[PDB]
Length: 137
RNA sequence: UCUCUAAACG
Image (cartoon, rainbow, N blue to C red):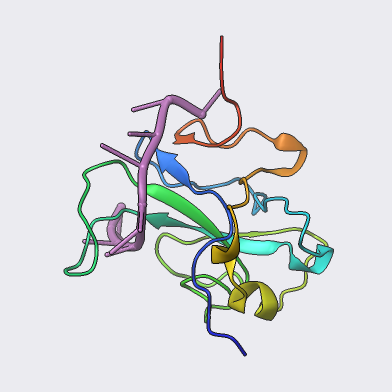
């Protein structure tokens, strides 16, 4: 198999406030045409860019938030709904609680990234900056 | 509550 591709396919949100990207009910799984109905299960996590030591640049900005598919991204070895700090788990009725082998080992670096967007274009948390809801007034 | 990475003004 190819190695674990570890990064998010999608656009990442940036913090304005201080409270974590905590959804109601487990409802917050994004849309992506190049994915099946079984695929639609995943988690949100933080990216403080705050360095434990070595191999990264302090930049002082607010933090970011990334999504991953189930059994993919940095927490790829957790099952669904696991009890770890700064992970927010999300699922659809229609998804399967299996890890995503192809989606978790293939190469995102091949193109542009996928716009993070909810079903119906449901407006993401006011605490955060997304690619939608641009321009005024 | 909680440290994680490629610049932000939904």
